[PDB]
Image 1 (cartoon, rainbow, N blue to C red):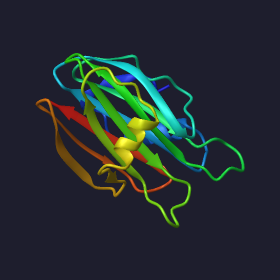
Image 2 (image 1 turned 120 degrees about the horizontal axis):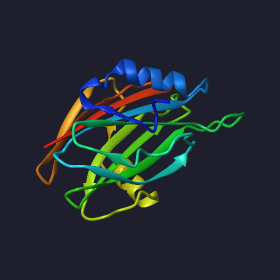
Image 3 (image 1 turned 120 degrees about the vertical axis):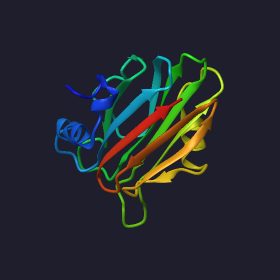
Length: 175
């Protein structure tokens, strides 16, 4: 499998993430995630809090510098109008937590995809509160556009998320 695995940070592309989407099988709402670590340190998985949907793989436990982690999620199968929404966190070698959120809703008649990345002081597990902190703060939109910002702690992030039902999200965390 590709999801739940790590690869050379330089080989992370949309082609790889699209293949991650294929791997998820045929479900109307899913997301492929690739996060390139260039923070000058290793990361260790904490957990993932899925508010909507689920995942079939486990968070790559270790992500060394120059490496990209691959992950994925999707809506529950069946006649349920739900999407793929979650927040997951990785513990950094600097002692802080990297928090990531993705929201892929079922109803684009009224909603859009949104995502965000944030660094939290210390060891912080992903939960409803972290989810609300990323989604209700100032999240980027899945607009097929690249965005970037400083995350404090001398680190920055540049990334992108697509706008439809089978979403791809690529992020790079640099120092």
